[PDB]
Image (tube, rainbow, N blue to C red; front, side, top):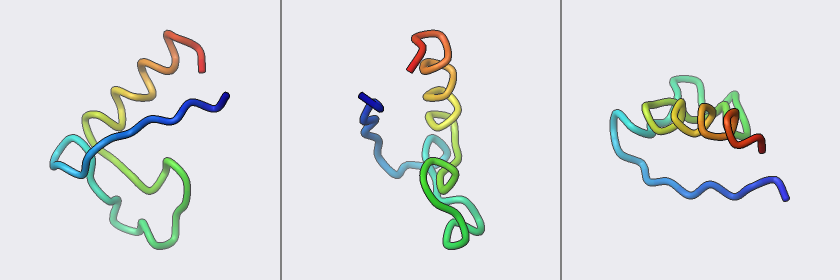
Length: 46
């Protein structure tokens, strides 16, 4: 089950990347929580 991570658009936690229109998936977003997500997912394995 590719986990569903919900988050809110609030700088600088989760923001729309510069060229977000030319990107898709998780690459569209950037911020504190965006990085925190990858870290949590790495230690929890998912």
